[PDB]
Image (tube, rainbow, N blue to C red):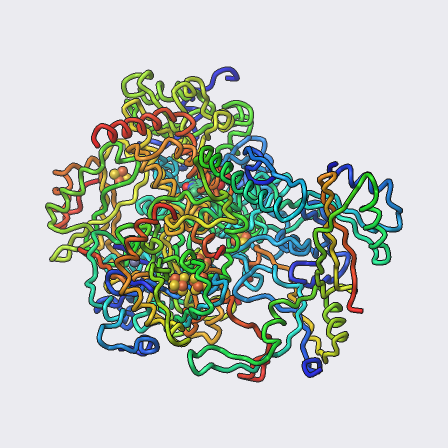
Amino acid sequence: EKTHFGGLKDEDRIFTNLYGLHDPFLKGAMKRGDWHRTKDLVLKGTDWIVNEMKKSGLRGRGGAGFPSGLKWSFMPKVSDGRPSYLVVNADESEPGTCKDREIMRHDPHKLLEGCLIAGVGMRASAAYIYIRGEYVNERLNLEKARREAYAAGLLGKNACGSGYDFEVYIHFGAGAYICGEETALLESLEGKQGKPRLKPPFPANAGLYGCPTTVTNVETVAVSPTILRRGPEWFSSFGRKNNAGTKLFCISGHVNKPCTVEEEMSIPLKELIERHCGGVRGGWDNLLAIIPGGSSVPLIPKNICEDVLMDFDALKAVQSGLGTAAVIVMDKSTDVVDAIARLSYFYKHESCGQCTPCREGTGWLWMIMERMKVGNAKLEEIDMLQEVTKQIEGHTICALGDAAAWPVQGLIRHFRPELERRIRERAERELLQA
Amino acid sequence: PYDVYDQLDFDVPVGTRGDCYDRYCIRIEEMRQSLRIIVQCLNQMPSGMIKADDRKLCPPSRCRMKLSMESLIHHFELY
Amino acid sequence: TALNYHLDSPDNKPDLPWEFSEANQSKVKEILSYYPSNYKQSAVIPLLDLAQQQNGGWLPVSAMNAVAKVIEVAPIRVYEVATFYSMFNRAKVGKYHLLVCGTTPCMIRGSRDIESALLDHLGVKRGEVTKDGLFSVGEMECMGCCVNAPMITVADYSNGSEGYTYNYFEDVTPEKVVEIVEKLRKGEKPPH
Amino acid sequence: EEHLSRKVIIYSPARTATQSGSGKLGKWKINFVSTLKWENPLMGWTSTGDPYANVGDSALAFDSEEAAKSFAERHGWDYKVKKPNTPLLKVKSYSDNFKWKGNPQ
Amino acid sequence: MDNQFIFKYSWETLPKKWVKKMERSEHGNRFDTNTDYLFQLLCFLKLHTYTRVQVLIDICGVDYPSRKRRFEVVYNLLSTRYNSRIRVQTSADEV
Amino acid sequence: VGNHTAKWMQDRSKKSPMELISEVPPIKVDGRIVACEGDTNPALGHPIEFICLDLNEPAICKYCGLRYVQDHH
Amino acid sequence: ALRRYPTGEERCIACKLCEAVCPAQAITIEAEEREDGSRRTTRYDIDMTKCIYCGFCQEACPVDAIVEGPNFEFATETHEELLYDKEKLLENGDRWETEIAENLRSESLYR
Amino acid sequence: RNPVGGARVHFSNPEDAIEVFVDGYAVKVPKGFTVLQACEVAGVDIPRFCYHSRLSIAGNCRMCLVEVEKSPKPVASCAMPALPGMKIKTDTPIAKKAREGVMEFLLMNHPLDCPICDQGGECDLQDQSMAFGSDRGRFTEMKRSVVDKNLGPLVKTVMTRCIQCTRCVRFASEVAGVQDLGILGRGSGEEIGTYVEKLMTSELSGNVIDICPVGALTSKPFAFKARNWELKATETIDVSDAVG
Ligand SMILES: Cc1cc2nc3c(=O)[nH]c(=O)nc-3n(C[C@H](O)[C@H](O)[C@H](O)COP(=O)(O)O)c2cc1C
Ligand code: SF4
Ligand code: SF4
Ligand code: SF4
Ligand code: SF4
Ligand code: SF4
Ligand code: FES
Ligand code: FES
Ligand SMILES: [Zn+2]
């Protein structure tokens, strides 16, 4: 309700095959409700689909949370000769996230019908599904579902008997985290190195092959048909205002029972962990720090986690983000400084190397963080560490550079005494030993 | 005044006749006043840098020039 | 020991002939059919993956030159792609590439307890193939969240492109990893 | 007298190609074309007997084309003026990197 | 007698046609004058009670080849009475 | 003995500096990178130079001519 | 004097900083790639009759190659003996190396 | 104000022109000019490394950052198109701080080679460090190092100096028409090279020496022979063919 959020029922769940108990193929998908009367939805026209998306309040599920309907409306109404492309981002290489993998594993037909619904809502003639390279088994599942849809007439020429021709193809990456970035995905799909582009141009004006293009997450695309069929007002009824709908959640780390669950948006973080995942290993008092969604947002401490809600606006106000809704939980036994230094290694390793502050700064951050892990640093280096993060942030081509500075900035902001102590203990050991 | 001459005590001898003998006595008295100043400089000599810190006008130390890119660039430019 | 350049060797040099097999020409044609005919370069990644599967799990420089010919680009543009992405092996690996020693999410649950036992049973160091040419150990790249598994990866290049599998194994222990190696040696696909 | 009948070139030196910075242009020089130098047969040092060996590049300078011309004509030198080349700024777009190739022919 | 007082008092008392340029700066108070007035300006400054510029420190020339009057002649002067310095400059050519 | 040295060295009793630095054996390093300062006291040497040892052939310091190699591989 | 490394290699790498800073223009340098690829002078002349013995060259050198040593007793009978070439300078370095090195150790705490 | 370098600006039509402000001053530029080109018309010299007027825009060095009103982030002027009413600031504390931070990152792994480097004395990196980033260096860790590459008898290579601007790669593809140079690898370990051992055969290959802003690509026959301050410059024409 309007007061409290959580406790989503089975009847409001969109992904009705999340645990893989039923058949994910065409017979089972039609049994669950997929490809049901799809012809009439597309005969309502592009303008109606975009309007329903706008009214549903759906926001981008890829981390940025941009409103989905406004983003589809960016596509041109009249073609200037160039075709229009829809690109589905199934390249989730962010540590701790598997929501898109589970969608491609147990509801591929939701993705395929979402691909067609989105394509009509974008006036796009073809769609490309960029899957992660190591999702080999998932891709083979998707290709089988795609072959099923083509034979049944649901995809291809005269899709579902409506006269709208729509091709769906499948592409896969080769193991690069940066290729999940929307412009880097476009470059990788063009057969080049996965290096992000500058903006402008924006993809809706010059994207794939220089043609108008929209890149959207698997989750965002896979929920459009259920929103269309059940209506935007049902979807907007969940969550707070501007944070509408339902979210796929995955909670890992120091919890009694980790699991991936579908839950109402803006659910309290504490309620989420205690209701679906038992609780912090050792009780809620044992909690030390939580990473709300994905390793690309800053951590929050125990006092902030007590009443922060799992939505875009709530986590923004405490200097964090919803991200991919990949909840990583750390109890008091974790070495937080080691955990952050381990993330700093990941961003140095995953940097595409194109632009100077990220290419050179990510390595510098990792080197300092490895030194601070054992206290082999001066107390004034913590301030210097803070300033190097500020030199990276806002000065890079893409948002990986910001995502590299945020975990370090959060550590200093919330656990500076721990770093200061490690420096003190090392200095005390240095004085007595020699 | 310039440098630290305002923090130092010394007399300015002047003549009364303006001939060669006054100028001889003044130069003698000026060496006694120079001796007086040197003593005060010796006693008031503080610790610190002997070169202006700005890094556009003063050479870096040899160790800095051989260890830091910025210092080497400045040394190359300065010389 | 991955390097951003190539040094000529008897089994890896540009004058060695290399082309897609006749049973692979059909796959090559259908891969190219997904993209506009004047945008063939979009096929570089799936074609490099298919070349890797045909050639036993690694890409000699001749294989890269062969893909560059199909997509009609200069070979340097293919070298850029093969060196940028980490799934491409530019040095020889065994018939079964074992990928271990994960990243951040699995080290918290003690992931660095599987590698040393693997090299000790296999009798090689990381990066070099065994004498019989069956097994090599490589750096795994991780997905997911590492909740219920110090995990390992197995790439099966022992049956070319028509028997290639890329599977992840859960709950792997210094014992269980060996059980995988022995079933892999005997030909049985280990359960995952 | 003797050094007042030499012919000079008045020109504005262009930008060096080894640097992208434009901070040395706008100056106007008087080139005395001092090309009479040889090697001293003791140490291999470069010798000259021409007094205007470097004054045209080291000391004399002018802020305008007219100033250099006026100075040359007052001294009686015969001058030729070489007008400097300038770049033409053209419309450049980053979006051009991703221009559509058109339909396959 | 600071440079603030000299600049203001010279503006009020000097005949206007003598000085064409007045620069007040921490580098030095400077009075640019035409050549036909240089002698009279220097006699005023020497004899006037409120200036008493009794010492001529030196005279130097500067060459400006890009100028119609290429030579600048600079008179550095000193008042021991008021502990102040003044710079008086004028331009000249070759003839 | 070479042409570069013969421009200035007119005495053949001692070896040229190019000969002398060639006789110093390459230094084995455990790792792929080594920093050379040209002296035990860094202030008395040359500006610090980081040298990569990925190539089989020994790597030369561009300031002092010392050669380095990877010890194991 | 011109100095060597303890291996016998020359310290000078022909940066030409000393030539540029020299107030008397007493230094002349020619250089080219050596047969082993090293950046070395083929000519290094100091005109001892133009030099003002200021020490600016020793300050400018980044590798401690050129130094003003402690010898002051080198009067000659001819002007040409005071035109020092590269080999004479390196001979001076060999003769005075023990004293020069000790002096540099002494003065390394001030520069 | 005189455009930078005295550069000429051509207008197809006076109607096809827009007004932008560069440090308060008002300039008129053709439609389609970038922020950097507007700054040149204003006579303001923006520091740059990856940008070359005769090559496609790359926007990777991040040295051309300026402040744009109502823009939340510093703006790469080389790539950003100019818009009517745009207020461009180049000397603000945000722009100055961005330049110092980027110059710090550029020199982090750069080798202490100015004495042995032929670019010394005519080096954009040297001049911009003296001007824009007047940072006392605080990087104390180990620098990365790169092995040199063989590109033939004309282009000598010292790749530790490379700042990965990709001017050489873009020149090879766009101007020379011979695609031999690429950027291999990923991250701080990316290296400019040909991957396989091959020499630069294009008849315009030597031009990569001029466009390389650092001493990574230099003329092998000119190596170590002279410093730029001791060379007399003469402007003349070439007689090797009938082009002049
Ligand atoms: C380093 C990086 C990695 C990213 N990875 C993904 C990803 O794996 N999946 C995804 O949907 N978006 C990813 N994004 C966000 C995309 O740039 C883009 O905003 C998103 O795919 C749009 O999807 P949406 O609007 O439907 O949420 C990534 C962004 C960055 C900077
Ligand atoms: S910020 Fe990092 S990942 Fe993004 S373009 Fe720059 S170097 Fe590449
Ligand atoms: S001492 Fe050295 S720097 Fe000074 S004038 Fe003599 S040669 Fe030149
Ligand atoms: S003596 Fe020193 S300063 Fe002079 S050229 Fe040699 S290395 Fe450079
Ligand atoms: S390119 Fe050469 S001259 Fe320029 S900063 Fe680097 S080492 Fe010094
Ligand atoms: S070699 Fe030179 S031009 Fe090429 S990327 Fe490196 S710095 Fe740029
Ligand atoms: S052990 Fe966790 S991904 Fe490899
Ligand atoms: S000059 Fe604009 S980013 Fe390199
Ligand atoms: Zn050395």
Q: What residue is shown at x 33% (from left), y 47% (from top)?
A: H142
As rendered, which of E28 and B70 lies closer to the eye?
A: E28
Q: Is residue H236 left or right of residue G66?
A: right
Residue H3 drawn above or below residue C177: below
Q: Is residue A364 left or right of residue H61?
A: left
Q: What residue is shown at x 28% (from left), y 66% (from top)?
A: C21
Residue A425 x %, y %: 28, 26
Q: Quadrant of residue D21?
A: bottom right
As rendered, which of B5 and H50 lies closer to the eye?
A: B5
As rendered, which of A192 and C107 lies closer to the eye?
A: C107
Q: Is residue G82 left or right of residue D102?
A: left
Total numbered labels? 0
Asked whether residue C81 is in view, the answer is: no
For ligand 5, the image quadrant comes to bottom left
Residue D67 drawn above or below residue A267: below
Residue A338 drawn above or below residue H148: above
Residue C31 x %, y %: 38, 58
Indicate the quadrant containing the N terminus of chain C: top left, top right, bottom left or bottom right. Answer: bottom left
Asked whether residue H47 is in view, the answer is: yes
Residue B37 drawn above or below residue D45: above
Indicate the quadrant containing the C terminus of chain C: top left, top right, bottom left or bottom right. Answer: top left
Q: Quadrant of residue C157?
A: bottom left
Q: What residue is shown at x 42% (from left), y 39% (from top)?
A: A404
Residue A220 x %, y %: 47, 37
Residue A159 x %, y %: 50, 47
